[PDB]
Length: 60
Image 1 (tube, rainbow, N blue to C red):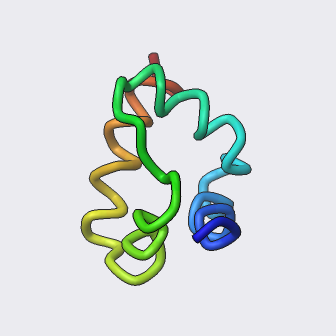
Image 2 (cartoon, rainbow, N blue to C red):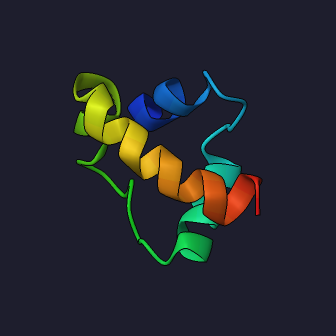
């Protein structure tokens, strides 16, 4: 539950590393292992986490 996170976020432009920082900016300490299930396998809830880190990080 590591490179599945990488594999999920590389669609956007995040390389998991910048996503990682933006998780803390969101204040949601996630994708640590076994969210990464949802990252690939539940793309509905994946898009929610991404949405929160998108405002918190990217578009902030």
